[PDB]
Length: 29
Image (tube, rainbow, N blue to C red):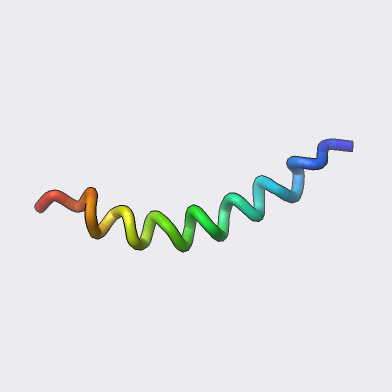
């Protein structure tokens, strides 16, 4: 049941790996 139960963790890394790039851009000192 709940196939997202995992995807959630997946989207976690990616996002956790993307934000690190976004934040830099959306940092807007």
